[PDB]
Amino acid sequence: QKLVFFAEDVGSNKGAIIGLMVGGVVIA
Amino acid sequence: QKLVFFAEDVGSNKGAIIGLMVGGVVIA
């Protein structure tokens, strides 16, 4: 394996996120 | 609101979970 690169990319985060694996009475 | 209940249930976890919110050199 050889990698040679002059890359640039943008992925960038501002939100309101709800990540449940679910259990809350998933209802809490 | 009124709640009255007798509830018994079962959700239990043993996993090899990958959760990415994406951005990884998602790669590569």
Image: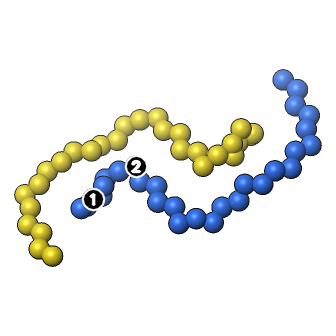
Chain colours: A yellow, B blue
Subunit that carries the residue with mark 2: B
Q: In this view, does A25 lie to the left or right of A13?
A: right
List x then y, in percent, for residue A23: 69, 46
Q: Name the residue under label 2.
A: B21
Q: Name the residue under label 1.
A: B27
Where is the C terminus of chain B found, in terms of image quarters? bottom left
Residue A3: x and y in percent read: 12, 69
Classify mark 1: helix, strand or loop: loop
Q: Which amino acid does label 2 sit on?
A: Met
Name the amino acid type tagged 1. Answer: Ile
Residue at (27% x, 44% y) in the render:
A11
Task: Work out whether residue A9 or residue B18 is closer to the camera in this orientation and state it.
Answer: B18
Using the image, determine if residue B4 lies above or below residue A11: above
Q: Position of residue A7 (x, y in %)?
A: 11, 54
- Left or right of B18: which side holds A11? left
Snapshot quadrant of residue B20:
bottom left
On screen, residue B6 versus residue B18, left or right, reads: right
